Image (cartoon, rainbow, N blue to C red; front, top):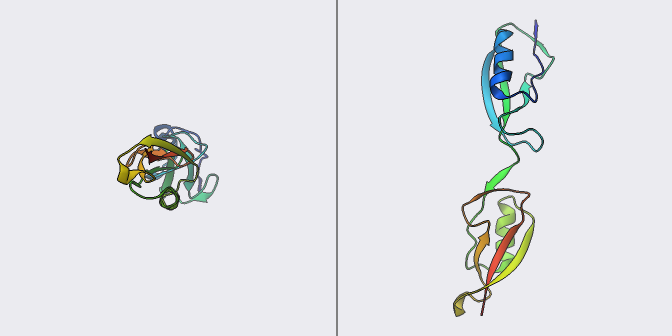
Length: 133
């Protein structure tokens, strides 16, 4: 068998060249990772140092950086509802802000920071802006 080289950390291009030089076929998967930078390799399947048949396909897990999610719209909800919905989307760190609104939005969410539909790391604090006035 041919040993799968350990390409964790290598750029996707460099890792793929290394694997190709050993005769492997390649498929890539793009996955979040908290410690390998974007476009660098997390690991392979089959894993580094495994012995496999010459020419076998190796799956190369390529980092897209830390996990990110799209911020859901939570406008006109209560703060409590907004926290539940943001939590369901993967976020967990929240702060409240006040900003002037029309009477019927007073006490309701008028937006977030980062704003709705923006992609954000799930480690980021999401400010939930509530109408005041």
